[PDB]
Length: 316
Ligand SMILES: O=C(O)[C@H](Cc1ccc(O)cc1)NC(=O)[C@H](Cc1ccccc1)NC(=O)[C@@H](S)Cc1ccccc1
Ligand SMILES: [Ca+2]
Ligand SMILES: [Ca+2]
Ligand SMILES: [Ca+2]
Ligand SMILES: [Ca+2]
Ligand SMILES: [Zn+2]
Image 1 (spheres, rainbow, N blue to C red):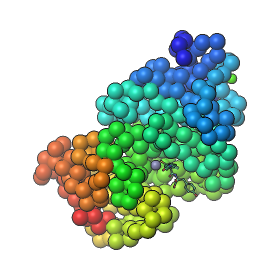
Image 2 (cartoon, rainbow, N blue to C red):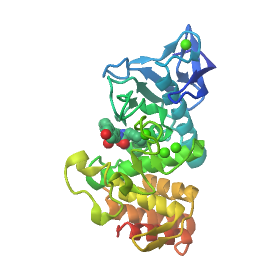
Image 3 (tube, rainbow, N blue to C red):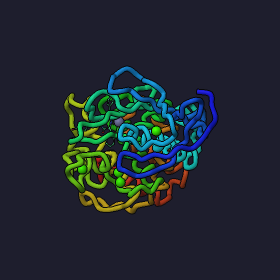
Image 4 (cartoon, rainbow, N blue to C red):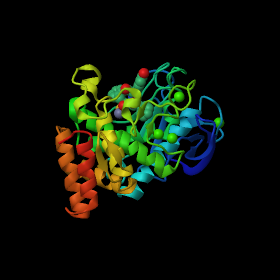
């Protein structure tokens, strides 16, 4: 929409008040003109037709419960855009400031969020397994990272390349969470998962096995469910990423952590420079070692830690 850029105020899914960038033209629209070609948030109105209607509001105040998921999807997409620009110097997901679109209130009681190759989509959850998925910053960053992956490595969504695709989204979703410093952790989806149970999360990077996911290649899922276990085998890569950053001893193998920043640097480089659509776990290890070498030298501790981390999770 063509209008005047302004700032509205609202309350997110978790009840927190935040300011959002909107556009004015008769109505106030969830259209942020301050980032690239814009950030647009749509109302799917509980249906499955996409993208739906560009979110319109009469007074620039978003405190209605219906508004909550829109506020967060819009706000978190901005934070995620900032992370990629400021930290990795990438302009939007395509690297050329492509408009970012998200639709909320997708379907009825839909327990998921996703990147469909064109935009992000968020369900409201059934109120038990999940509350509106855009309420979690690691969720929003996870979905937008899929867009980055689409325009770079293009990791096919199945088997090992799919598990890598998923892990990259969990890894960058977590780095964005730390970046915004929103009660950061190495857990995935803790803010929107199971509103009745506290202290749990959908997945864990620090300890994947906590929620039944493999933390070692010998324990990888080899079946056909979940596109060959993309949300299962990602635990192996998530564990490796956690080890590279924080360090620790896993299955007797010791890893000296090099921190989050270098983790982000190494993985972003591997993703955009070395990974291809069919890359498997072994190739990711080679990509990660190569990236750390490019950035820090072959005799660097950074290269050493990447090797130990993959050794620790059994990926040769
Ligand atoms: O496995 C998934 O798809 C789970 C959803 C799930 C999990 C358990 C459950 O009982 C029901 C639904 N989705 C995801 O992990 C994340 C959402 C999320 C991220 C971070 C934190 C929390 C949630 N979504 C995905 O991975 C999307 S990208 C998977 C997908 C692809 C294509 C079409 C539809 C869905
Ligand atoms: Ca309003
Ligand atoms: Ca958190
Ligand atoms: Ca988290
Ligand atoms: Ca919970
Ligand atoms: Zn995903």
